[PDB]
Image (cartoon, coloured by chain):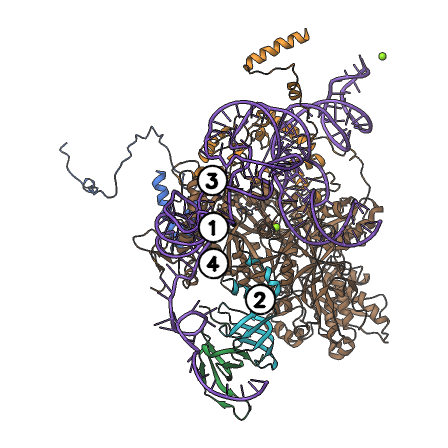
RNA sequence: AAGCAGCUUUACAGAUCAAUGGCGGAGGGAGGUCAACAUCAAGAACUGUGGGCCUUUGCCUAUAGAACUUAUAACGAACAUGGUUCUUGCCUUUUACCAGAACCAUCCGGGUGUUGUCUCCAUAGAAACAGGUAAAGCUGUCCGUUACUGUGGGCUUGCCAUAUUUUUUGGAACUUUUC
């Protein structure tokens, strides 16, 4: 989703350059700009065990503005007549 | 508007047509924009590789310019108990600073000291990226009723609102393009005077290429240096051309026919001339 | 205007200024202003009645001056050309 | 073969002004000002002088059609066949132009274009000494790199006003393609960077200190110039100076009112962006892309600029350069910034007090001038001189004194006669004009002219005076030897190939030592000539002028070598003796303090707005004992008995006959110091200079008779012998110089550089600066000079042209060579680099054989040993204790 | 618009002639854009130097319109 | 950048409708795989004109114009061949050759400037007259609007503040001697 992700970068770049920031936070934010030119090669290591067709693609398209039912209740004990 | 006339000299184009010829020519384009890529590969360094009897590793190999190098002059000067060895003097050192590194430099032409370190940013992934854009890999810039003018005072160009025109992304790409793309005006050259494959052997080949081509890149450079080294200038008093003096004669007449007809006529004429 | 610009050209040049009071101050020009008030160095002063003295430094208000004499060479100064 | 120069008087290009009015402006010292353009490498300096010249001359014969269009820069001032081929300024060159500012007051200005390359930092020292103010031209992409940091610190030191040109603004948009708000931030980041280094004065575009320029496109402006052209009509005349104050500096404009905080409901940029950068980028955008007719309407409507019918049929880069030269006129705002920055009352007294001794102003009867350098200007040999007092005509006769004499001759002139100075005749005076000399009958006070007929009298600098009365000779001030910023360290030892061609070489070596000021040429006892230079490119410039220009013979040339220095790391019956026992000296040696050595390298002794220069460091012995006791914590006795500071070294009298008879010592003191100078110049290890050793005169014997003839001539070689005994006993070491490195590489190519620093021996990267707004970053590090042979091109071949380094010797960093110098068992492999523990033995043993001090068949090691100086019976006593190997 | 440049003179004893006949010499403290000049320890010079001279006041200000010329007696 | 005024024009109504003055006009415009003739590598370099010195040349000084080509140097962003000489290679003789050098040429091309020709398209003449060159209104005579207004366009313009100390909204007025 490069197009909106450029727009996330552009507003995030506007933070350092035109606005004052606390010091300890500031060197971590420009470190992200340093990893950007190193092309994210230190955030791309994980356990890709599943093939892209072995993982059945259930890309759950939920948003964080939905009330998400908070199903705590099935972790309790109940009584199967089933 | 584009050509001067049917004599077909002096073409003149516009921006849209020029970027269109640019995008078609991608296969045969030079595709290098900084001159610093040609650091030890320019022809001044080829002349010094010839004159000093050195071999640039991609460069061509030439006979010794001074074959009588065999003599050694006995002296205390260059002896091993004199010399301090820290860095081995590579041949690239001898070509880059030719009057420093090697004694007896003669018929040696000065090379050109580096052009400024070229950072030119091209955008190729998305046409919807604008002309002016803070590209990746660019370091960020971390930093930081009294008076009244008449209203409707404005900047100079403020009546025009768009900074980026639809042709600016093309025009800046034409601005850095190597000749002749940047020109958008020029004269006609002959069909054999355009050297399409010239830029290929004027660049470094590859690592992946086999040793069969890598010689063929060297042999074409060796031809290229010898043409540049010995220029044969034309004389100005050559006013009698062959076709023009034959045209003045009553025994030669002029017409227009097809090329393949003119080829078959020449094969029949040439067969009769020998027979 | 050009006439004042010319006065800047005079600067550092021995110039003669006649006051509307009648005096004459001839000497070097230290400074000038758009107002036209001129201050001189090593001026030889001529009173209106002719008595001549010598003053180390001087400043004269612009309004007072009747005319200024500037170096003849200035005439071909670059600014003057119409086109 | 040597220069492209116009030799005919008739072919000298005419100016737009008459040029006679310019010569009459030379009568006025206040009218003429001398600006020297200095900067980093390839920053557009010579191209900046291209703009001044072609706007001053009506038609140049040298200017071609690719030059008239935007295709190739016309490098007028580069001038030399050597410089055309490198594409690099090698020599100082200049022009003298009449220039008009915004207020249209014409004033004559002498320009000097200093070379940007860091090996030619000696040439810019000539430019700093010549110039009233310096115009420091900055690449906007590189920003403030470290070589900019030195130039801004030097011009503060030389009491020279500064004016800054940010150059190559096209690269900000045509190369880097920054959005306009980002480019403001780039410009704001640079101006913040220069303001941190000028501690005295803020530099800001409102202040008229800072000039924006894009030289290849050939336009320059200040914000004051740009308002007066195009915004002066629209606003009332009282408002204009207040308006341009609001222009830069984060205050915003919309519908007639200014406010510091951002405008609500409005997408807004700062005022400098809205009024300057946004129209400038629309000029770049529309000259490249807009239809020519619709562009032609905007230029009449907004800039009142008519495009020609011929100018419509241009290529895009010539059309862009043409429009910007129509919008931005001749360089008035640059000239205006030069005028407003220079204050002669503030600095001209301090500058002459810096180049000479501080004193009262010499009278106007004295002719008094400073001869900067000898110039190999086209077809002849000219002296570059600047006149500080009096009037000079052709055919005059002038006392011309070399500045190496001026230490004694000034110190003599205090005097609590005749034949003082050689007299040469002023043969011919000319104004430099780049590619030509305009001959002139007389040369007034304040202007820089070229004089033929004075170069035979001096080497590397001179003072030039014609005095009227003998009493006025008491007042006159001599010029100090010129401070070239880089010390010459790189060694080349050259022998002519044909021995019969030797005196022709000696002519050229005397000839080069005039033209190249930074070069130290010496002759050794072996007949081999040693040349000291700044770097690789400096030597390659040196040897081409040697082989091709000056001496047509061929020469044998050694490898790259470096000057070493000799020191000690510990303090050390310590005594010395001669053949005839009438004299006995004892000398101790000690390492000097690291802060003490570092400040003496800075040519002044002190700390915290209190410092004493080395020239008058003897003249305040009470104040000197205050500084040594307070700042460095020495003893009170050691503070009072210091005799002399020779370069990086010190002598202290610590003896009991000084408590007995110091007046007997005082009549012999001046030649102990003369013998001390005779010992530091050639040390005991390898005939190399001594650096950073605290000498203590432990004792001195006076024989039972006084002969002023014999005792004087005998103690001078024996004190030099006695200093060796102190140093060799005191655990001697060998020092090597350290280049500091300034690498500019793209950000992905940084691990290539880090591996490239590991292949060298004593290299370390100390600081890595993200150059903002650019994909490249600055790397600051160090390298030994003996390791920096071909360091410059190894970097580039590995980075494929995206890397560049500047090697320089600003800070005089001398570092201990990692071996032990007295190792009889050090393994020196032939034809390979010796390992790290064998280095101090190797560098001395080879140096002793270049000099001829140690003579072996192939490799015989008689090390620098404490037995040829001390008696051999005492040397066997030293072996049994384990003190001496 | 532009301030007159008296800057070097200030703190120096100065003689200046005002309007028709009068000459006044005093230390000069302040100047403005109209040239109005205020100087302290003012004295009105006349033919007889010690005699007809009379001091004016501790502080005196002068309209710039009546100034004909200013000469500083001093460095 | 609007408006007003000034300037320039303009479709003009004009003053004159004379002598005038300005700008234009006194034998086209675009072309051609058309031609001829000049010219195209040198103190970083050219030519015309005026003045002075020596006695034409040459120098010095003043002035006017410089097309094309050239600086990481060359008409050509391209790139062959031959000759002589020297030094190699191949190794039965020669020719053809190997691949450096030095000096010369040939060949395929190119720019520019004049003049002529050819093709296509043209029509207001006042394009009327008289002189002459290697060239032309080259010159004289001349004709178109017209030199002084008002409307309508453009700006080489006003500095947009027009009375309150440095300029243009008054420190002015009056009387006296000498000659
Ligand atoms: N893009 C760009 N390049 C420029 C500009 N000015 C100069 N250059 C180029 O930068 C290089 C160096 O320019 P120079 O004129 O040699 O500058 P310099 O500072 O005199 O250089 P040195 O001789 O090294 O001292 C050349 O290739 C120029 O064409 C500019 O404004 N923009
Ligand atoms: Mg330069
Ligand atoms: Mg036979």
> Of the residues tagged 1 and 2, which is closer to the observer?
2
Distance from the alpha carbon under mark 3 to that under mark 2: 50 Å
Colour displayed for chain E in the image of the structure: green
Please identify the residue farthest to the left as the structure is shown.
A81
Q: Residue under circle 3?
A: B172
- As measured in the structure, the alpha-carbon distance from the residue carrying label 3 to the one carrying label 1 is 22 Å
Between marks 4 and 3, how big is the CA–CA gap? 30 Å
Q: Which chain is orange?
A: B
Report which colour depicts chain D. brown
Left or right of residue D809: residue C59: left
Judged from the image, the quadrant occupied by ligand 3 is: top right
- Which one of the lettered chains is coloured purple? F
Q: Residue furthest top?
A: B275
Q: Which residue is mark 1?
A: D772
Separation of residues labelled 4 and 2 (CA atoms): 25 Å
Judge whether residue D716 can be spotted in this image.
yes
**Marks 1 and 2 on same chain:** no
Q: Are marks 4 and 2 in contact (CB under 8 Å)?
A: no
In front: mark 4 or mark 3?
Answer: 4
Task: Answer with the quarter of the image where residue B126 lies.
Answer: top left
Q: Marks 4 and 2: which is nearer the front?
A: 2
Return the mark for residue D224: 4
- Circle 3 sits in a helix, a strand or a loop, which is it? helix
For the residues beneath circles 4 and 2, the answer to whether they share a chain is: no
Asked if F77 appears above or below C16 in the picture, the reply is above
Q: Do marks 3 and 2 share a chain?
A: no
> Which tint was used for chain C?
cyan
The residue identified by callout 2 is C10
Some atom of ligand 1 lies within 8 Å of the CB belonging to the residue at label 1: no
Element at label 2: helix
């Amino acid at each position: 989703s490069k197009k909106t992700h450029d727009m996330i970068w552009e507003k995030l770049r506007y933070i350092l350059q035109t606005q004052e920031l606390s010091s300890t936070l500031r060197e971590s934010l420009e470190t992200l700009f340093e990893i950007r030119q190193k092309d994210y090669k230190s955030g791309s290591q994980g356990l890709f065990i599943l093939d892209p067709t072995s993982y059945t693609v259930h890309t759950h398209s939920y948003i964080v503005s939905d009330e998400d039912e908070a199903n705590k209740e099935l972790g309790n004990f109940e009584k199967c007549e089933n | 508007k584009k050509v001067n006339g049917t004599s077909y000299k002096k073409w003149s184009f516009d921006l849209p047509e020029m970027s269109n010829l640019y995008r078609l020519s991608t296969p045969l384009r030079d595709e290098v924009t900084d001159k610093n890529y040609y650091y030890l590969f320019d022809k001044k360094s080829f002349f010094n590789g010839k004159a000093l009897n050195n071999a640039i590793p991609g460069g061509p190999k030439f006979e010794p310019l001074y074959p009588r190098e065999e003599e050694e002059d006995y002296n205390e000067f260059n002896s091993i108990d004199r010399v301090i060895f820290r860095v081995p003097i590579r041949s690239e050192y001898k070509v880059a600073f030719p009057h420093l590194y090697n004694s007896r430099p003669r018929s040696v032409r000065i090379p050109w000291y580096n052009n400024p370190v070229s950072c030119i940013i091209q955008n190729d992934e998305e046409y919807d990226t604008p002309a002016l854009f803070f590209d990746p890999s660019l370091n960020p810039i971390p930093h930081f009723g009294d008076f009244t003018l008449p209203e409707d005072f404005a900047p100079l160009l403020a009546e025009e609102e768009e900074l980026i025109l639809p042709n600016t992304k093309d025009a800046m790409s034409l601005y850095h393009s190597p000749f002749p793309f940047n020109r958008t005006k020029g004269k006609m050259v002959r069909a054999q005077d355009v050297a399409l494959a010239k830029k290929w052997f004027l660049q470094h080949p590859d690592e992946e290429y086999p040793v069969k081509v890598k010689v063929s890149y060297q042999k074409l450079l060796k031809n290229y240096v010898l043409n540049e080294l010995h220029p044969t200038l034309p004389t100005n008093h050559n006013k009698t051309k062959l076709l023009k003096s034959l045209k003045n004669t009553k025994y030669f007449q002029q017409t227009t026919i097809d090329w393949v007809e003119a080829g078959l006529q020449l094969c029949r004429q040439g067969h009769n001339m020998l027979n | 205007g050009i006439p004042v610009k010319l006065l800047n050209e005079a600067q550092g040049h021995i110039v003669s200024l006649e006051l509307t009071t009648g005096a004459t101050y001839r000497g070097k020009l230290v400074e000038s202003e758009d107002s036209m008030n001129v201050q001189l160095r090593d001026v030889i002063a001529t009173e209106p009645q002719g008595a001549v003295t010598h003053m180390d430094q001087i400043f004269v208000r612009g309004s007072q001056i009747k005319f200024i004499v500037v170096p003849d060479l200035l005439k071909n100064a670059p600014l003057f050309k119409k086109n | 073969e040597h220069t492209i120069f116009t030799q005919l008087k008739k072919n000298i290009p005419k100016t737009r002004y008459n040029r006679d009015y310019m010569l009459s402006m030379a009568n006025i010292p206040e009218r003429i000002i001398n600006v020297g353009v200095i900067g980093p490498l390839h920053s557009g300096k010579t191209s900046l002088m291209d703009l001044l010249v072609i706007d001053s001359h009506k038609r140049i014969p040298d200017m071609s059609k690719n030059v008239e269009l935007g295709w190739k820069p016309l490098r007028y001032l580069d001038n030399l066949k050597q410089e055309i081929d490198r594409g690099l300024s090698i020599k100082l060159n200049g022009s003298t132009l009449l220039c008009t500012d915004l207020e249209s007051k014409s004033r004559m200005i002498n320009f000097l274009d200093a070379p940007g390359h860091v090996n030619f930092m000696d040439e810019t020292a000539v430019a700093l000494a010549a110039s009233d103010l310096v115009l420091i031209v900055i690449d906007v992409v590189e920003g403030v790199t470290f070589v900019v940091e030195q130039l801004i610190k030097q011009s503060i030191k030389n009491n020279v006003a500064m004016c800054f040109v940010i150059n190559k603004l096209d690269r900000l948009i045509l190369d880097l393609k920054l959005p306009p708000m980002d480019a403001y931030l780039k410009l704001n980041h640079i101006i913040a960077n220069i303001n941190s280094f000028t501690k005295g004065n803020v530099f800001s575009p409102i202040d008229n200190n800072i000039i924006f320029a894009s030289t290849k496109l050939g336009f320059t402006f200040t914000i004051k110039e740009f308002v007066s052209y195009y915004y002066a009509h629209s606003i009332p005349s009282s408002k204009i100076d207040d308006f341009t104050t609001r222009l830069w500096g984060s205050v915003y404009y919309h519908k007639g009112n200014f406010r510091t905080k951002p405008f609500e409901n409005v997408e807004k940029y700062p005022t400098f962006v809205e009024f300057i950068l946004i129209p400038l980028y629309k000029i770049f955008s529309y000259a490249l892309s807009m239809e020519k007719d619709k562009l032609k309407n905007l230029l009449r409507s907004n800039f009142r600029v008519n495009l020609s019918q011929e100018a419509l049929q241009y290529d895009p880069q010539p059309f862009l350069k043409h429009v910007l030269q129509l919008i931005f006129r001749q360089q008035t705002g640059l000239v205006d910034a030069i005028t407003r920055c220079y204050q002669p009352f503030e600095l001209f007294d301090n500058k002459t007090a810096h180049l000479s001794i501080p004193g009262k102003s010499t009278p106007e009867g004295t002719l008094w001038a400073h001869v900067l350098k000898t110039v190999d200007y086209g077809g002849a040999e000219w002296s570059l001189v600047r006149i500080y007092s009096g009037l000079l005509k052709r055919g005059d006769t002038v006392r011309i004194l070399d500045t190496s004499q001026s230490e004694s001759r000034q110190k003599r002139q205090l005097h609590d006669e005749d034949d003082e100075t050689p007299s040469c005749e002023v043969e011919e005076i000319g104004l430099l004009g780049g590619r030509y000399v305009y001959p002139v009958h007389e040369a007034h006070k304040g202007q820089i002219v070229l004089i033929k007929g004075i170069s035979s009298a001096y080497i590397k600098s001179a003072t030039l005076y014609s005095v009227k009365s003998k009493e006025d000779m008491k007042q006159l001030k001599f010029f100090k030897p010129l401070d070239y910023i880089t010390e010459a360290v790189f060694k080349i030892v050259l022998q002519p190939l044909l021995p019969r061609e030797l005196p022709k070489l000696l002519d050229a070596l005397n000839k080069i030592s005039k033209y190249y000021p930074g070069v130290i040429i010496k002759v050794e006892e072996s007949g081999e000539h040693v040349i000291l230079g700044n770097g690789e490119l400096y030597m390659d410039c040196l040897l081409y002028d040697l082989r091709a220009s000056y001496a047509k013979i061929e020469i044998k040339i050694s490898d790259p070598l470096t000057v070493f220095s000799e020191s000690c790391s510990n303090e050390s019956s310590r005594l010395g003796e001669e053949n005839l026992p009438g004299l006995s000296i004892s000398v101790a040696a000690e390492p000097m303090d690291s802060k003490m050595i570092q400040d003496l390298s800075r040519n002044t002794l002190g700390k915290g707005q209190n410092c004493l220069d080395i020239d008058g460091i003897m003249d305040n012995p009470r104040k000197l004992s205050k500084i040594l006791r307070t700042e460095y914590g020495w003893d009170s006795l050691a503070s009072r008995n210091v005799w002399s500071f020779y370069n990086g070294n010190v002598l202290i009298n610590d003896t009991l006959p000084d408590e007995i008879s110091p007046e007997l010592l005082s009549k012999y003191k001046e030649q102990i110091i003369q013998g001390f100078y005779w010992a530091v110049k050639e040390g005991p290890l390898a005939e190399e200079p001594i650096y950073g050793v605290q000498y203590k005169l432990l004792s001195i014997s006076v024989p039972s008779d006084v002969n002023i003839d014999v005792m004087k001539s005998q103690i001078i070689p024996l004190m030099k012998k006695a200093c060796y005994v102190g140093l060799l006993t005191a655990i001697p070491i060998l020092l090597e110089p350290i280049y500091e490195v300034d690498i500019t590489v793209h950000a992905p190519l940084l691990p290539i550089v880090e591996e490239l620093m590991k292949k060298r021996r004593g290299s370390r990267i100390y600081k890595t600066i993200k150059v903002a707004g650019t994909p490249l970053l600055e790397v600051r590090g160090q390298v030994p000079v003996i390791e920096s042979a071909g360091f410059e091109t190894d970097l580039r071949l590995s980075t494929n042209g995206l890397g560049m380094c500047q090697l320089y010797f600003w800070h005089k960093i001398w570092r201990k060579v990692p071996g032990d110098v007295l190792d009889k068992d050090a393994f020196i492999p032939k034809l390979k680099p010796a390992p790290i523990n064998s280095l101090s033995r190797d560098f001395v043993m080879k140096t002793r054989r270049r000099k001829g001090i140690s003579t072996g068949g192939f490799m015989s090691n008689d090390g620098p040993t404490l037995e040829k100086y001390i008696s051999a019976e005492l040397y066997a006593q030293l072996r049994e204790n384990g003190l001496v190997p | 618009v532009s301030t007159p440049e008296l800057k070097k003179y200030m703190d120096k004893k100065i003689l200046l002639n005002i309007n028709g006949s009068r000459k006044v010499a005093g230390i000069l403290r302040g100047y403005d854009i109209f040239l109005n000049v205020v100087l302290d320890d003012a004295m009105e010079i006349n033919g007889e130097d010690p005699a007809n001279n009379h001091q004016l006041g501790l502080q005196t200000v002068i309209r710039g319109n009546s100034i004909i010329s200013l000469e500083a007696l001093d460095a």
